[PDB]
Image (cartoon, coloured by chain):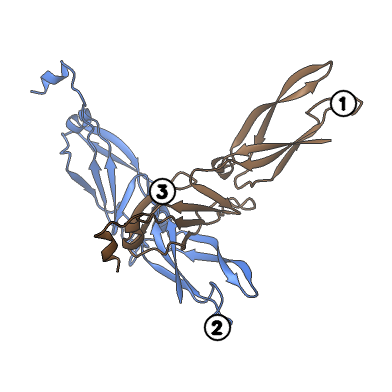
Chain colours: A brown, B blue
Amino acid sequence: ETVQVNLPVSLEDLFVGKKKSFKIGRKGPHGASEKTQIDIQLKPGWKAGTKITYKNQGDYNPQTGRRKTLQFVIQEKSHPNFKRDGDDLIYTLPLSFKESLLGFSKTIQTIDGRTLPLSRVQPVQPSQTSTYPGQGMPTPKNPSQRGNLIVKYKVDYPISLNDAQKRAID
Amino acid sequence: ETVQVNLPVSLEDLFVGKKKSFKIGRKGPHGASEKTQIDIQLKPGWKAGTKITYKNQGDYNPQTGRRKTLQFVIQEKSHPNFKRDGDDLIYTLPLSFKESLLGFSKTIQTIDGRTLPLSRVQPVQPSQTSTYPGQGMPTPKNPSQRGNLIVKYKVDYPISLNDAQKRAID
């Protein structure tokens, strides 16, 4: 029997191939409650659903002095900015009605640590997506290669254009 | 129709004329989602806004088996130290109240890889700029030639000169 444990990690962790270390409870011999240490070396670009089984290290008993195997399944914690899709990251930029039409100068924190400025002088199509090649997650195969970054905009609209407001528009 | 994609690169990349390689998504034939590989050979000294169109390689359809052309526009990622202005690099040196007046011995990492020591024995005018010819970006025309380097200083001031402090000054 295998035991599947969900392993919550951050996009930051598997972007750099971070190392996870924690303890898990397991039923030991002679009615005991033990806690085994586990260290998982995440590889840059690792995805959700990827497994890492640790043979015999769980509960105790195939009617013979042994333990169930543990199988960790990488799950990625929600990121306040980035949503992951394969090799790349999708980010939603909150624009204001004004800058959605006039243009904007924004600077956001990428996934590696550097900062990427998002600039635009032309009106932005609310349902439009802009793509920044190479700013996504590293590709598991060749971590040297990164997916892209997709930016979406959440153009905030005026709830009640007052009087004066309710005019110019036309 | 042309598709303009912002290509984020580093000052380090276009200083050496680095090679960029990545994949971009494109709608293929028969309702398909493809990803085309692109390799761009940046020339030393390349600037922001410079384009590199790849004829027919994007989405699919001038109502006839063809693809939209892709146009990459070089954008330069923000550098933690250098700000670029034409052919040269502007760098801000954090000085301390003491060294802003007394003098300093600093060593910073240039854009090529070598190290340039910044030294001074005299008080530094807070709004002053020092110029180091040839330490900027290579000139696209003759990469052998480099722009200059401008150093600015961010002289940190004492927030509350305590008692004793609040005296000597005068």
Foreground mark, 3 or 2, reads 2
Residue holding disc 2: B63
**Which tag, 3 or 1, sits closer to the chain's start?**
1
Q: Which one is in front, A101 or A58?
A: A101
Q: Which chain does the numbered disc 3 sit on?
A: A
The structure residue drawn at horizontal position 16% and vertical position 34%, both measured from the top left corner, is B122
Q: Circles 3 and 1: CB distance less than 8 Å?
A: no
- The residue sitting at 52% across, 65% down in the picture is B39
Q: In the image, what residue type sits under mark 2? A: Gln
Task: Tell me, yes or no, whether dots 3 and 2 are on the same chain.
Answer: no
Q: Secondary structure at mark 2?
A: loop
Kindly identify which residue carries mark 3.
A108
Q: Residues within 10 Å of mark 3 (few under 14, many from 20)?
A: few
Crowdedness of circle 1 by 10 Å Cα count: few (<14), some, many (20+)?
A: few
- How far apart in space, not on screen, are marks 3 and 2 (Cα)? 39 Å
Q: Residue A121, how many percent across, how many down?
A: 32, 63
- Residue A110 percent location from the top left of the image: 46, 48
Q: Are marks 2 and 1 on the same chain?
A: no
Return the x and y of residue A20 as percentages of the image width and height.
Answer: 62, 33
Query: Is label 1 in a helix, a strand or a loop?
Result: loop
Q: Which residue is mark 1?
A: A61
Instruction: Indicate the amino acid at tag 3.
Output: Ile
**Quadrant of residue A160 in the image?**
bottom left
- Letter of the chain that mark 2 sits on in the rendering: B
Q: Residue at x 38, y 66 (%)?
A: B50
Residue A145 quadrant: bottom right
Toward the left, the furthest residue is: B170
